[PDB]
Image: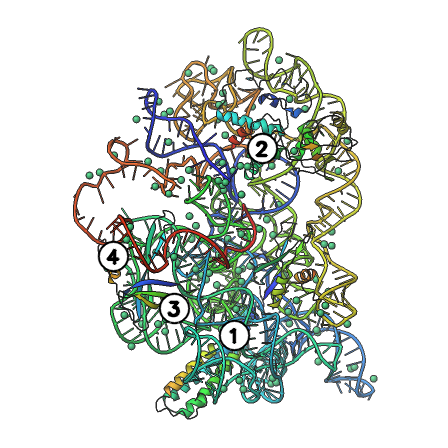
Amino acid sequence: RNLSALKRHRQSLKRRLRNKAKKSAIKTLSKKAIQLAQEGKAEEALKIMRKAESLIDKAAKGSTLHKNAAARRKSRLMRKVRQLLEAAGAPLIGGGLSA
Amino acid sequence: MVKIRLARFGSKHNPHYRIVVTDARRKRDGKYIEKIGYYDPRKTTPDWLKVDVERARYWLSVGAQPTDTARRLLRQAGVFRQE
Amino acid sequence: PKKVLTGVVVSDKMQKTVTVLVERQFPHPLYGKVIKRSKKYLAHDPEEKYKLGDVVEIIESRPISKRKRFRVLRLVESGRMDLVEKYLIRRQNYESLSK
Amino acid sequence: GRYIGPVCRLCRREGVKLYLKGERCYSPKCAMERRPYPPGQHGQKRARRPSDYAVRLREKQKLRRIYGISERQFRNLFEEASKKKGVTGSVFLGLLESRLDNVVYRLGFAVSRRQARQLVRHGHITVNGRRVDLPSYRVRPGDEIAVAEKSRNLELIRQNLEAMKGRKVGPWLSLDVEGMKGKFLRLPDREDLALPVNEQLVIEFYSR
RNA sequence: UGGAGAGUCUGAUCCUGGCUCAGGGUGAACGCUGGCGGCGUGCCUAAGACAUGCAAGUCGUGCGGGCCGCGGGGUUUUACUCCGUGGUCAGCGGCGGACGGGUGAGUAACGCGUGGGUGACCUACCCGGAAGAGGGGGACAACCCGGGGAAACUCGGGCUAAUCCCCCAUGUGGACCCGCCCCUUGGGGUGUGUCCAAAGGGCUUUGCCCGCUUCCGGAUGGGCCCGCGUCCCAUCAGCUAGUUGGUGGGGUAAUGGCCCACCAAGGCGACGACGGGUAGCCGGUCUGAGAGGAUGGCCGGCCACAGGGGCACUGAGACACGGGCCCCACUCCUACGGGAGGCAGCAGUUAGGAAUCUUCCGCAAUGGGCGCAAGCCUGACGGAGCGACGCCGCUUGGAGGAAGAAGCCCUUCGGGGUGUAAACUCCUGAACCCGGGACGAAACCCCCGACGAGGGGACUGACGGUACCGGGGUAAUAGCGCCGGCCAACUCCGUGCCAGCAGCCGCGGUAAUACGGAGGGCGCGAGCGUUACCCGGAUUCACUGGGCGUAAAGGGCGUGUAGGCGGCCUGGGGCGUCCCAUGUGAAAGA
Ligand SMILES: [Mg+2]
Ligand SMILES: [Mg+2]
Ligand SMILES: [Mg+2]
Ligand SMILES: [Mg+2]
Ligand SMILES: [Mg+2]
Ligand SMILES: [Mg+2]
Ligand SMILES: [Mg+2]
Ligand SMILES: [Mg+2]
Ligand SMILES: [Mg+2]
Ligand SMILES: [Mg+2]
Ligand SMILES: [Mg+2]
Ligand SMILES: [Mg+2]
Ligand SMILES: [Mg+2]
Ligand SMILES: [Mg+2]
Ligand SMILES: [Mg+2]
Ligand SMILES: [Mg+2]
Ligand SMILES: [Mg+2]
Ligand SMILES: [Mg+2]
Ligand SMILES: [Mg+2]
Ligand SMILES: [Mg+2]
Ligand SMILES: [Mg+2]
Ligand SMILES: [Mg+2]
Ligand SMILES: [Mg+2]
Ligand SMILES: [Mg+2]
Ligand SMILES: [Mg+2]
Ligand SMILES: [Mg+2]
Ligand SMILES: [Mg+2]
Ligand SMILES: [Mg+2]
Ligand SMILES: [Mg+2]
Ligand SMILES: [Mg+2]
Ligand SMILES: [Mg+2]
Ligand SMILES: [Mg+2]
Ligand SMILES: [Mg+2]
Ligand SMILES: [Mg+2]
Ligand SMILES: [Mg+2]
Ligand SMILES: [Mg+2]
Ligand SMILES: [Mg+2]
Ligand SMILES: [Mg+2]
Ligand SMILES: [Mg+2]
Ligand SMILES: [Mg+2]
Ligand SMILES: [Mg+2]
Ligand SMILES: [Mg+2]
Ligand SMILES: [Mg+2]
Ligand SMILES: [Mg+2]
Ligand SMILES: [Mg+2]
Ligand SMILES: [Mg+2]
Ligand SMILES: [Mg+2]
Ligand SMILES: [Mg+2]
Ligand SMILES: [Mg+2]
Ligand SMILES: [Mg+2]
Ligand SMILES: [Mg+2]
Ligand SMILES: [Mg+2]
Ligand SMILES: [Mg+2]
Ligand SMILES: [Mg+2]
Ligand SMILES: [Mg+2]
Ligand SMILES: [Mg+2]
Ligand SMILES: [Mg+2]
Ligand SMILES: [Mg+2]
Ligand SMILES: [Mg+2]
Ligand SMILES: [Mg+2]
Ligand SMILES: [Mg+2]
Ligand SMILES: [Mg+2]
Ligand SMILES: [Mg+2]
Ligand SMILES: [Mg+2]
Ligand SMILES: [Mg+2]
Ligand SMILES: [Mg+2]
Ligand SMILES: [Mg+2]
Ligand SMILES: [Mg+2]
Ligand SMILES: [Mg+2]
Ligand SMILES: [Mg+2]
Ligand SMILES: [Mg+2]
Ligand SMILES: [Mg+2]
Ligand SMILES: [Mg+2]
Ligand SMILES: [Mg+2]
Ligand SMILES: [Mg+2]
Ligand SMILES: [Mg+2]
Ligand SMILES: [Mg+2]
Ligand SMILES: [Mg+2]
Ligand SMILES: [Mg+2]
Ligand SMILES: [Mg+2]
Ligand SMILES: [Mg+2]
Ligand SMILES: [Mg+2]
Ligand SMILES: [Mg+2]
Ligand SMILES: [Mg+2]
Ligand SMILES: [Mg+2]
Ligand SMILES: [Mg+2]
Ligand SMILES: [Mg+2]
Ligand SMILES: [Mg+2]
Ligand SMILES: [Mg+2]
Ligand SMILES: [Mg+2]
Ligand SMILES: [Mg+2]
Ligand SMILES: [Mg+2]
Ligand SMILES: [Mg+2]
Ligand SMILES: [Mg+2]
Ligand SMILES: [Mg+2]
Ligand SMILES: [Mg+2]
Ligand SMILES: [Mg+2]
Ligand SMILES: [Mg+2]
Ligand SMILES: [Mg+2]
Ligand SMILES: [Mg+2]
Ligand SMILES: [Mg+2]
Ligand SMILES: [Mg+2]
Ligand SMILES: [Mg+2]
Ligand SMILES: [Mg+2]
Ligand SMILES: [Mg+2]
Ligand SMILES: [Mg+2]
Ligand SMILES: [Mg+2]
Ligand SMILES: [Mg+2]
Ligand SMILES: [Mg+2]
Ligand SMILES: [Mg+2]
Ligand SMILES: [Mg+2]
Ligand SMILES: [Mg+2]
Ligand SMILES: [Zn+2]
C-alpha cells in the first residue's frame, strides 16, 4: 500500500485551481468587454479587450490554453467587439483592432 | 522519441537480434519502422553483423537515438567513421 | 485522391442539401454474374443550384454535418426524371408487402 | 527406439530375403532357407488372394523394414520427397540411401543395418573429421565418412574391413580400406539400387 | 506437382437417398503404459471471489528543512552562534506513472481489414535551423504552534527556498481583427494596430556541460472523415424527434446535431431499414486437387475493458488496471459517528470444471523509466521448475547361435507353431563415476585525442559447473490397440437370445475366426487407444459441381409491378472487361 503517486494527485489539485482561476478571469473580462461594445462605449470596450487579450495569451504561456485554443477566444472576441461596435461605430481607442 | 535498438528474434539460448528503427514506446519485439541489420552475439556464422550504414546514417539525421549496444555495433560498421 | 462519384439527385426537399443516388457495377464474388448495387449520398448544395433529375458528380469533402461528407462538383447531365421515376416506383412498392 | 527383436522372422513375412541379419542371411541358416513361408501357426496354410490394399501395405513394410526405421521417420521422409522437384519415387530412395547408418552399412563398415546403427550411435563414425553419432544424419554428396582413429584398433572394425578387401562398392560410393575412410559421391539412382521393392506401390499406398 | 473409395433397403437388379467408416487436425481431456534430452506449450469453464509477497519509479547537477552523529571556528570560561561533512526521513519542484503486462466481457460498429482525405488537426522527449534570457514582486508545503477524531485522517495560526507562481521590459518571431496579393474550403505572404517570451544548476568557474524561452522545419506517434468488404433469423417490415437539414452560437488540437437556440419537414428501408440472436477483428491457422468450409489459442497489428454504472481533474497525451470524485453489490476495520479495499500484472489459494504449472533464480544479457554521471527501479524480459500436451532426435543391444532345448499352443498323433527368438560365445558401452570446462560479453566507464572520428585500456553472469570435450565403464524400460466385412492379421477351449460385443451392416438361442481367455498373428511403438470438436470423403447447398414425368421437388391458373435478360447495321463515349508502368500488399508464417 501507500504509493507516492499520490504526490501527483496532490499537485493535480494545485494546478486545478490555477487553471480554473485564470479561466474565470478570461470569461469575466470578455463578457465585460462585449457588454460595453453592445453598449456603444468604444474606448472602454477597447481598453478592456486589450487586457482580455493579454490575459488570454498569458494563459496559453502555461498548460491551460496552450494550443490554438487561445487563438479561438482571441478571434471570437475581436470579431464580436468590432461587430457590436457597429452601432454608431466611432472606434475611439482603436488600440486593439486594425485600421 | 524514435530510437535505434535491438529486437530478439532467436530461440531459447540461441539469440539473434534485428537492429531496428522503432518508437521507444512499442514493444522490444513489436512493430518497428525499418529493419536496418542483424546481430548474432554468439558469432556462429562468418557474417554475424550487417548494417547498411547509409540507411543508419539517415535515421541519425532525423533524430533517432541508438542504444549503447546499438551505437557500439554501429561504430563497428563505421557509421561514425568520418575520414 | 478524394473519392469522386457520379449519380442522380432524387431529393430536393432539404435545405442546401440534395440526395444523390450512385449506382455501382461489379461481379459477384462467387457466382460471378454482374450485379448492380446502389447507395444514396447526402450532398452539400450551398447555392441550391442542382434540381431533381440532375446527374451530378459528387466528391469526398470535409464533413458538413452528420451524414453529409460530400459536395456537388459539377452538373454532368441535366433533367432525366426517368432515373428518378425508377427510384420513386421502387420506394412506392414498399407500401405493399406489409400485412 | 526402432524395432528390436527377431529379424529373420521378417525375412519370412515379406517373402523376400532381408539382409538385416548381416551374415547368416547369406549362409543357409537365414530361415529364408527351407522356410520361406510366413511365421505363425497359419504360416503353412494357403494364403488368400491379397486385397488391392493388402499388396500396397506389404510393399511399404518390405521397404521400411529393410532400412530399420520407425514409421514416424519413414512417413516424414516421404512427405519430404513429394514436395521436392523430381520423381517422388526415386527421390525417396536416394533420401533413404543418404541415412548415415545406411551409408555405414553400404560402405561395408558394418555387416548389417542394425550393426551400422550401433556404430554410429556410439560415435565410432567420423563425418568430415567430426564425430556424428546420429543414425538419422543425412549425408550430402562429397562428405567423407571415416572411422574414428579411437576405434581403428577395435577388432570388430578390422574384422569387417578384412573381408572388404577386394570387395567392390556401389558406383555412388568409394572407400579407402587401410585408412578406414569413405566418401559419398552422389545420390544413387533407381538403377543403382537392387532393392526388391516397387516404389509406385508405396506411393500408391500413401494416396489414401 | 494435383482429384482412390467402401458397407448398408432386394430373393436378386439398377437408380435415388440418408447414415456410417478409412484420412488429417487440436490450448485438448480420459484409460492403460511410460526411459533420456532439445525446442515449443500449458484456466477453452466463473470477466467468479481472492490470503501473502513482489509487479513504477527516479533525480541532492532544481530548493529549503526535521531527526541522530562527527570535525573546525568567534569566547579566558559559559551561554549563544558561524562553517564543513556523514547517515536518514519525507516535503516543495521536474520527468515518468497514457509505455510496458493482462483479459475477450461489451461491441454487427468506420470496431476491424483495405485503399484514400485532412484546405479540419495535435504530437512530450529526439534531430536541423534562426533568435533571446533584462529587472522586480509573491505564496504553499516541510518545519513550528493549537484543536477535533477510535481510526482514516482533518481543521485553524505563523516563518521559508527554488528550475513553484505573478508583473514590467526586450519582439528574432508568433498569435488575433481588418485590408491587399497569390492560392483555392481554415494554404502561403504582406501592411497597420493590439497581445505574447524565459530559470537556473554544475564544475577541470573566462569557458564549457545539463537545462530554460519564442518561432520554422524533420522524424515518430496519434485524432477525425471517406470508398469498399465484414455471421444467422423475414415466424423481425416498416424505423426515426436531435430524427433529417438549415442559420447562428457553444465546445474541441480539429470537421461535425458533438451539444444549444431558432427555422424548414425532412432522413432510413426488400440492394434487409428497425428488432432479435450470436461474436472482438485481422495477419494467419486447419482442411481441401481446387473453389471452398472451418477457426482466430500461442506470436505480431488494431480495438475494447479493469467488480457493475456514471463523471470529470491533472497533462503533449487518460476520462486513466496498480490516479480522483459519486451511486450500487460484495469483503474487512468500527469506539456505530465513520472509514479501508478492488490480481482480466507475476506466482499462489478457492470455487466451478473432463481439464490447465512454481507463492522459483536473476539485472548477466535485451528493452523501457529517471539521472551529467555513478547508479536506481523493471514478475517487460532472460532463464530454471513441473505436465509425453505437441514436435523432433535417442536408448532398452550388435554379431555368431540347433533342419532347431524347456514351457505354453495347435495336431490327421507322423508332426506343425512361438523361432535365431532364448540359453550360451564374442564385441560395443544408455546410465553412472573422475578431471577440464564455455560461447551468449561489449559497450556504459576510465585514459590518450577536443567529452568528436579514431585508438588504447578496465569491471561486468541467472542459466551453471549447465552445455561441450577428454578418461573410465555396466547388456541395460515395452507398451497399447486390433485380427466377421470396410481393413492388415486364425486357430483351440469356455459360454448357449445367457454373460456380453457393437462406428455402420451385425454377432451369441450348442463346432461362434464377431462374446470371454489362451497360443499365434497384424499395426504403431514412449507411446497406444478412446471420447468430444473442425475439415475431409460429401459432386449430400452442386461457382468450379446437382436436380424436380413416376425417386425429395413446377406454384391451381392468369395478369402485371420491381428486378433479371436483350435481333440486325453504323458512330461517339470508354462504366463493366482486357493490357502496360507504378505505389501498396509491415514483420513472422507459407
Ligand atoms: Mg514524484
Ligand atoms: Mg464570474
Ligand atoms: Mg488540457
Ligand atoms: Mg504506440
Ligand atoms: Mg554521421
Ligand atoms: Mg580525411
Ligand atoms: Mg576530415
Ligand atoms: Mg432544395
Ligand atoms: Mg451545418
Ligand atoms: Mg466546388
Ligand atoms: Mg411508408
Ligand atoms: Mg502431397
Ligand atoms: Mg516451381
Ligand atoms: Mg516429388
Ligand atoms: Mg552416382
Ligand atoms: Mg493426398
Ligand atoms: Mg512429384
Ligand atoms: Mg500443371
Ligand atoms: Mg507445367
Ligand atoms: Mg498444389
Ligand atoms: Mg440390412
Ligand atoms: Mg449390396
Ligand atoms: Mg424397397
Ligand atoms: Mg437382406
Ligand atoms: Mg451413397
Ligand atoms: Mg481421427
Ligand atoms: Mg521445457
Ligand atoms: Mg477465461
Ligand atoms: Mg522485485
Ligand atoms: Mg546529502
Ligand atoms: Mg566549540
Ligand atoms: Mg585558529
Ligand atoms: Mg560548552
Ligand atoms: Mg547551512
Ligand atoms: Mg544529510
Ligand atoms: Mg527526495
Ligand atoms: Mg496507474
Ligand atoms: Mg497496454
Ligand atoms: Mg499471455
Ligand atoms: Mg446486433
Ligand atoms: Mg441491424
Ligand atoms: Mg476503414
Ligand atoms: Mg461499414
Ligand atoms: Mg487506414
Ligand atoms: Mg516571502
Ligand atoms: Mg523571492
Ligand atoms: Mg498550515
Ligand atoms: Mg498559512
Ligand atoms: Mg510584454
Ligand atoms: Mg516582426
Ligand atoms: Mg504589425
Ligand atoms: Mg525571475
Ligand atoms: Mg515557469
Ligand atoms: Mg509530418
Ligand atoms: Mg454494412
Ligand atoms: Mg432543439
Ligand atoms: Mg454549426
Ligand atoms: Mg432563420
Ligand atoms: Mg443499399
Ligand atoms: Mg460476446
Ligand atoms: Mg494445405
Ligand atoms: Mg468464412
Ligand atoms: Mg471470421
Ligand atoms: Mg490475442
Ligand atoms: Mg466500464
Ligand atoms: Mg473482478
Ligand atoms: Mg467501472
Ligand atoms: Mg506531462
Ligand atoms: Mg480507458
Ligand atoms: Mg491490480
Ligand atoms: Mg491485496
Ligand atoms: Mg472441484
Ligand atoms: Mg511455465
Ligand atoms: Mg537524458
Ligand atoms: Mg521493487
Ligand atoms: Mg518467460
Ligand atoms: Mg516341436
Ligand atoms: Mg540376435
Ligand atoms: Mg569395455
Ligand atoms: Mg560472456
Ligand atoms: Mg568474449
Ligand atoms: Mg553497468
Ligand atoms: Mg584530457
Ligand atoms: Mg572510441
Ligand atoms: Mg558460474
Ligand atoms: Mg565418454
Ligand atoms: Mg538383455
Ligand atoms: Mg487402417
Ligand atoms: Mg481381412
Ligand atoms: Mg472387442
Ligand atoms: Mg460348450
Ligand atoms: Mg449355430
Ligand atoms: Mg465351442
Ligand atoms: Mg475368436
Ligand atoms: Mg475375442
Ligand atoms: Mg497376442
Ligand atoms: Mg518419438
Ligand atoms: Mg464430415
Ligand atoms: Mg463440398
Ligand atoms: Mg470433392
Ligand atoms: Mg444433407
Ligand atoms: Mg450449379
Ligand atoms: Mg464456368
Ligand atoms: Mg440430386
Ligand atoms: Mg413427386
Ligand atoms: Mg400445373
Ligand atoms: Mg403440387
Ligand atoms: Mg445486344
Ligand atoms: Mg439493358
Ligand atoms: Mg476503361
Ligand atoms: Mg511476407
Ligand atoms: Mg523471410
Ligand atoms: Zn534373414
Mark 2, residues whose alpha carbon is within 10 Å: few (<14), some, or many (≥20)?
Answer: some
**Amino acid residing under circle 4:** Arg
CA–CA distance in space, label 3 to label 2: 68 Å
Residue E387 spot, x, y in % from top left: 59, 41
Q: Are marks 2 and 1 on the same chain?
A: no
Earlier-in-chain disc, 4 versus 3: 3
Tell me: is circle 3 under 8 Å from ligand 9.
no
Residue C60 spot, x, y in % from top left: 39, 66
CA–CA distance in space, label 4 to label 3: 30 Å
Residue E508 spot, x, y in % from top left: 42, 19
Q: Answer yes or no: do the residues labelled 2 and 4 have beta carbons within 8 Å?
A: no
Tell me the tag on residue C63: 3
Nearest-to-viewer mark from 3 and 2: 2
Nearest-to-viewer mark from 1 and 3: 3
Please state which of residues C21 and B68 is positioned toward the viewer in this rendering. C21
Residue on which disc 1 sits: A13
Query: Does the image show residue D110?
Result: yes
- Secondary structure beneath disc 4? helix
- Secondary structure beneath disc 1? helix
CA–CA distance in space, label 2 to label 1: 82 Å
Q: Are marks 2 and 4 on the same chain?
A: no
Residue on which disc 2 sits: D90
E300 over E508 or under it: above or below: below
Please state which of residues E427 and E337 is positioned toward the viewer in this rendering. E427
Q: Are marks 1 and 4 on the same chain?
A: no
